[PDB]
Image (cartoon, rainbow over all chains, first blue to last red; front, side, top):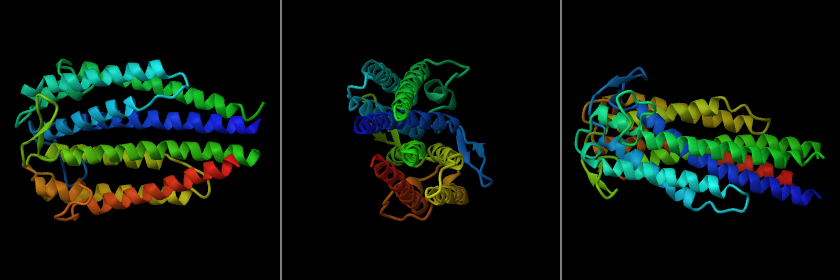
Amino acid sequence: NLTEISKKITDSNAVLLAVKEVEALLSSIDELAKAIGKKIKNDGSLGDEANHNESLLAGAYTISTLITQKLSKLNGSEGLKEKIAAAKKCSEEFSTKLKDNHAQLGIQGVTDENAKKAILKANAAGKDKGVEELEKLSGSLESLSKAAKEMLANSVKELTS
Amino acid sequence: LTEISKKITDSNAVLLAVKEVEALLSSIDELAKAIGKKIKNDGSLGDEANHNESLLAGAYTISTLITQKLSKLNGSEGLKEKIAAAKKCSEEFSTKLKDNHAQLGIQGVTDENAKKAILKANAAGKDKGVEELEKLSGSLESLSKAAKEMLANSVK
């Protein structure tokens, strides 16, 4: 029956698209981390302008709460409920850790070093102001993403049996 | 059924890249709301004006991620031209940001100039990047409709 398969595909694709939106929000924070202590140069490269990171981190913070918000609305019956919940828990822990470090992350003149302990994956100087939570959230959304992609693959495969 | 199987497969992948590019644009909208702001103990944003240079560098590096995602999107006939158009718009957006480095790449980037670069519908003007951002957003909307329409005609 082609109709049953047609709905299976559209529903699997819709869940994948919803998950990939959250993972792209996460990937944008990785892009923000590249800009810590940087300014745009005339030639398109980045140059140093150190320790003015507060509004960059403020942007990273509201993206992180947008991640939690979008994950809170995903409740289908497909079977990803436990992977979704694990990602939402990680997203809350990341936002709470940022907010909890406002004395270094929410002042005029936030330093490069403190910003990197918040959003730079694999930061060498430490991970105590958000990075550990960011890495876990990243892995949690990536697991979910691969899982929803494999569901879409198996639904599209049913077209030919 | 053969025709439809390809159209589903080709439209899904384009939809995938587009929705992830649109999420990157939503991240730039969050950056725009954070202009001149800092984090507070309760999660709200408080005012701390005119230090937007790394925020703008962050928007800029996102804009190059958008272009790279669009440049490797290698789609089917009937979507290829809308892909190429979106790629061109994303390039014009990054170019306009860098061309305005005299206001956007200095120590102490002002709230006013940051808003003319990344805040959609900024009241004082759109002359440092917003016009290109609005055009890129419209170009992605055209592409999204065309690819989602192929999936619909495919469910026939």
